[PDB]
Image 1 (tube, rainbow, N blue to C red):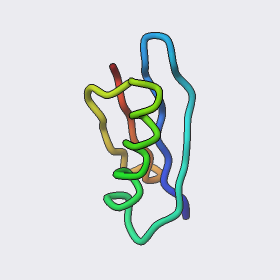
Image 2 (tube, rainbow, N blue to C red; image 1 turned 90 degrees about the vertical axis):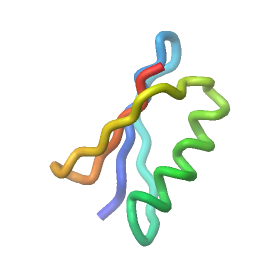
Image 3 (tube, helix red, strand yellow; image 1 turned 45 degrees about the horizontal axis):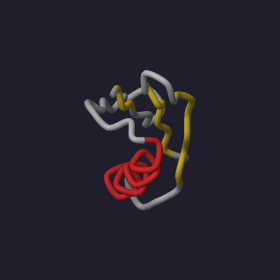
Image 4 (tube, helix red, strand yellow; image 1 turned 180 degrees about the horizontal axis):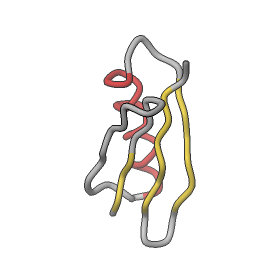
Length: 56
Protein backbone atom coordinates (compact mmCIF):
# COMPACT_ATOMS: atom_id res chain seq x y z
CA UNK A 1 0.00 0.00 0.00
CA UNK A 2 1.33 3.49 -0.85
CA UNK A 3 0.21 6.83 0.64
CA UNK A 4 -1.23 9.54 -1.67
CA UNK A 5 -1.58 13.35 -1.60
CA UNK A 6 -3.29 15.80 -3.99
CA UNK A 7 -1.82 19.29 -4.55
CA UNK A 8 -4.58 21.94 -4.35
CA UNK A 9 -2.44 25.02 -5.09
CA UNK A 10 -4.02 28.02 -6.88
CA UNK A 11 -1.43 27.58 -9.67
CA UNK A 12 0.29 24.25 -8.86
CA UNK A 13 -1.76 21.03 -8.57
CA UNK A 14 -1.62 17.26 -9.27
CA UNK A 15 -1.12 14.18 -7.05
CA UNK A 16 1.73 12.25 -5.35
CA UNK A 17 2.36 9.06 -3.33
CA UNK A 18 5.16 7.81 -1.06
CA UNK A 19 6.19 4.57 0.73
CA UNK A 20 6.91 4.64 4.49
CA UNK A 21 6.07 2.95 7.83
CA UNK A 22 2.97 5.18 8.20
CA UNK A 23 1.32 8.13 6.40
CA UNK A 24 2.48 10.35 9.30
CA UNK A 25 6.14 9.76 8.36
CA UNK A 26 5.51 10.05 4.59
CA UNK A 27 3.31 13.19 4.85
CA UNK A 28 6.31 14.96 6.47
CA UNK A 29 8.35 14.21 3.32
CA UNK A 30 5.33 15.13 1.16
CA UNK A 31 5.28 18.50 2.98
CA UNK A 32 8.90 19.02 1.92
CA UNK A 33 7.78 18.45 -1.70
CA UNK A 34 5.05 21.08 -1.16
CA UNK A 35 7.75 23.43 0.22
CA UNK A 36 9.15 23.67 -3.33
CA UNK A 37 5.78 24.44 -5.00
CA UNK A 38 4.79 26.84 -2.19
CA UNK A 39 1.31 25.29 -1.76
CA UNK A 40 0.90 24.82 2.02
CA UNK A 41 -2.43 25.61 3.75
CA UNK A 42 -4.84 22.90 4.99
CA UNK A 43 -4.31 19.15 4.42
CA UNK A 44 -6.88 16.36 4.96
CA UNK A 45 -6.41 12.58 5.31
CA UNK A 46 -8.82 9.97 3.84
CA UNK A 47 -9.52 6.44 5.15
CA UNK A 48 -10.38 5.40 1.54
CA UNK A 49 -6.86 4.53 0.31
CA UNK A 50 -4.68 6.49 2.79
CA UNK A 51 -4.72 9.64 0.61
CA UNK A 52 -4.15 13.28 1.66
CA UNK A 53 -4.69 16.91 0.58
CA UNK A 54 -3.09 20.40 0.69
CA UNK A 55 -5.03 23.53 -0.39
CA UNK A 56 -3.09 26.83 -0.56
